[PDB]
Length: 123
Ligand SMILES: [Zn+2]
Ligand SMILES: [Zn+2]
Ligand SMILES: [Zn+2]
Image (cartoon, rainbow, N blue to C red; front, side, top):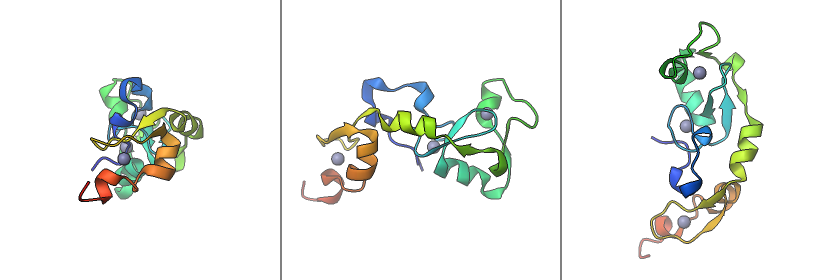
């Protein structure tokens, strides 16, 4: 139930600003809500499946503000600056035993869903 990328991908380079406000994993196709908090596209869509919702991150961080801290489709946008930054980070496959290495973007487009440890049962 974790849409975001396993924190294992970044390893020691793991940073808080690269994490989804919802699943707490590395941002996957990030959107930025009106309040500034980032969410994986999948995570935000799920949260907003039944309409607007209060931003849990705003609450927990004690900065909740009426109106601005409300997650809404009309005020959330693709955070391409965040996406580009995260895609440029050095990454290693999360599969315990895999040696694949490259940028997170290369992981998403070339390795994810094509991992030997996951697809080859006799590995
Ligand atoms: Zn997420
Ligand atoms: Zn927020
Ligand atoms: Zn792998």
